[PDB]
Amino acid sequence: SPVFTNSTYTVLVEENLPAGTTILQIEAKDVDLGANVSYRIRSPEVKHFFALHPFTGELSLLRSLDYEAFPDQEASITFLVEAFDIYGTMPPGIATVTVIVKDMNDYPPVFSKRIYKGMVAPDAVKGTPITTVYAEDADPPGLPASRVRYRVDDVQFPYPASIFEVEEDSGRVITRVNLNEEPTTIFKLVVVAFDDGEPVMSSSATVKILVLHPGEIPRFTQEEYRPPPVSELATKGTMVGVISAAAINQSIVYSIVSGNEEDTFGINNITGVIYVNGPLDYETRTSYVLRVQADSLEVVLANLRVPSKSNTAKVYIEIQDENNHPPVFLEHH
Ligand SMILES: [Ca+2]
Ligand SMILES: [Ca+2]
Ligand SMILES: [Ca+2]
Ligand SMILES: [Cl-]
C-alpha cells in the first residue's frame, strides 16, 4: 500500500492552456518493493477534464480550462487520486488534488470598423484633428484586461506612421508634425488597439487619409435651391433653375447624385444649369427633390468624390398643373 509524498496537492492553472499540458506530477512510494507504483484517477467525473499517466504520475488537461465557465467562486476542481503497488493490492494509497483555475484575459479589443476614412490638408500644422477610432473590449469592465489603448503601427506602412499619430487614450488621430504632402494622396495608417491583460491582446484597423485643402471643396451658394414652378407642358431643354458654387483655384463640376432616376431632368455639369430632359405629367408626378453636388476638377480627374456639408445641396422642383379647372359648384357626395 503506497504512501503519497504529499497527502494533498493544490495547483493553480491558467485558463486557456491547450489540451495536453502537464499541470502536476504526483508521487507515492511502495515501502516494500521501492518500485513499479502506478496511479489512477478515482473520481470518475473529472476524466472530463484530466488524464493521469498511470506510471509517471503526470496529470494533464484533456481540454483547455475556462475560468468564466464555472459558477461564481467555484472555479476549482477537487478530486481523489489513488496509487497501487505492482500487484494492484487493495486498498491503494489515496490523495486529494485541487486544481484552481486562474482567470486570464480572453478577448482582444475590437474596432468599430475595419476601415476608417478621414481628410487632412497638405500643409496641416502639427496637431490637426483628422478622425477618431474606437474599440471595445469584451472582458470584465473596469479591469486592466478591458482597458483600451491605441497606437499606430509602422510594420506594413511606415511612412504614415511618421506623419500621423493617435492619442493613446482617446483614439483621436492627428498630424504628428507639420505636413507637406500632395493633394489627392491617400495614406493608409495602421492603428492598433491593445489592452492590459495577462497576456496582452490587440487587433488593428486602417485609417485611410485623403490629402486635400478644405478650402478647395466647393461651397454652394445655398443649402436648398427652390426654383419657380416648372410647367407640366415644358418642352425638352426648358430651363428649370441654376445651382452654383465657388472654390479656391478650381474649376467646378456639377452633378445630380440622386432623385432623378427617371432622367426627367438633366444638368449641364459646367454651367450648373438644370433643364427639363424628359416629358412631364402633373397626374403622374407633382414634385421632385434632387440631391446635387459640386466637385473640384482636381478631385474628379483623380476619380474621387468628396461629399461634404457645403458641396451638397437639395433642389426642390415643383410641377405646375395645367389641367386644373374646377367647376363653379358640384352636386357632390
Ligand atoms: Ca474564458
Ligand atoms: Ca477571463
Ligand atoms: Ca481584453
Ligand atoms: Cl501613435
Image (cartoon, grey):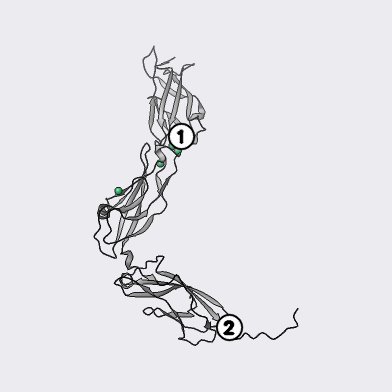
In x, y percent, where is residue 303?
A: 33, 70
In x, y percent, where is residue 112?
A: 42, 52
Pick out the residue farthest to the left.
180
| Residue type, numbered disc 2 | Asp
- Label 1, secondary structure: give it: helix
Tell which of 61 and 31 is nearer to you.
61
What residue would you read off at disc 1?
67
Tell which of 98 and 233 is nearer to you.
233
Tell which of 227 and 166 is nearer to you.
227
Q: CA distance from mark 2 to mark 1?
A: 73 Å
Q: Is residue 50 above or below residue 238?
A: above
Tell which of 333 and 70 is nearer to you.
333
Query: Are the residues at dot 2 and dot 1 in contact (C-beta closer than 8 Å)?
Result: no
- Label 2, secondary structure: give it: loop
Q: Choose the circle earlier in sequence order: 2 or 1.
A: 1
Pick out the residue farthest to the top.
32
In the image, the residue with mark 1 has its CB under 8 Å from the nearest atom of ligand 2 = yes
Residue 77's tag is none
| Residue type, numbered disc 1 | Tyr
What residue would you read off at disc 2?
321
Residue at 40% x, 19% y: name it. Answer: 37
Question: Of circles 2 and 1, which is in front?
Answer: 2
The quadrant in which the C terminus is found is bottom right
